[PDB]
Length: 168
Ligand SMILES: CCC(=O)N1CCN2c3c(cnc4cc(-c5c(C)ccc6n[nH]cc56)c(Cl)cc34)OC[C@H]2C1
Ligand SMILES: Nc1nc2c(ncn2[C@@H]2O[C@H](COP(=O)(O)OP(=O)(O)O)[C@@H](O)[C@H]2O)c(=O)[nH]1
Ligand SMILES: [Mg+2]
Image (cartoon, rainbow, N blue to C red; front, side, top):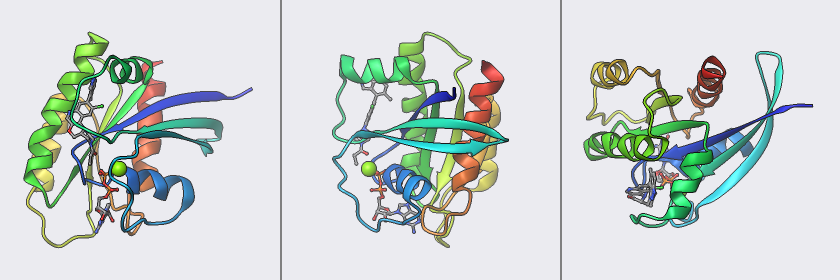
């Protein structure tokens, strides 16, 4: 039948990993979503005429290492590294998430997409050029997104699925 793509969404607390995922799946913006809930969500989509089942792990809880998390990253086929465009700290943190994923995959060609979320906000502290330059250095696409307006949301996840396809 149809292909499954195991996607993992990573990034600092409060960048809108949950909000991106609920927007994608349910078409609503959640103004407040339990910061602690870490769960996988499944949704069937059409991408370039191919029917695709996405299984999306939305990370949350606490800053702690677990062999369970290593297992989710190990099974994960592709990653969305999410920061918020009004939060330089979340941008500085991208490095750390990407390093942990590489730690477990023990490899360099892992499908990933850099995502600058909350693009609906006027109060930017990370310029597009900076994020572009980072994504160039990582060898991965950059997509600006807004969970609130939906701008870029389908593009982000579809781009990651195409990145997984290009690798497989
Ligand atoms: C509002 C709360 C929130 O959103 N979070 C999401 C992120 N979470 C994390 C951090 C910092 N480092 C993290 C590292 C890993 C992680 C990766 C990426 C890969 C392999 C791993 N093995 N064990 C842990 C691993 C993960 Cl899943 C989560 C982290 O700070 C905030 C906290 C809670
Ligand atoms: N303006 C705006 N707010 C957002 C957006 N994405 C998430 N938020 C808000 O930022 C907060 C954190 O979002 P959440 O999805 O819980 O962050 P997570 O901790 O990364 O799961 C919530 O109050 C969300 O409404 C966005 O694209 N634009
Ligand atoms: Mg969340």
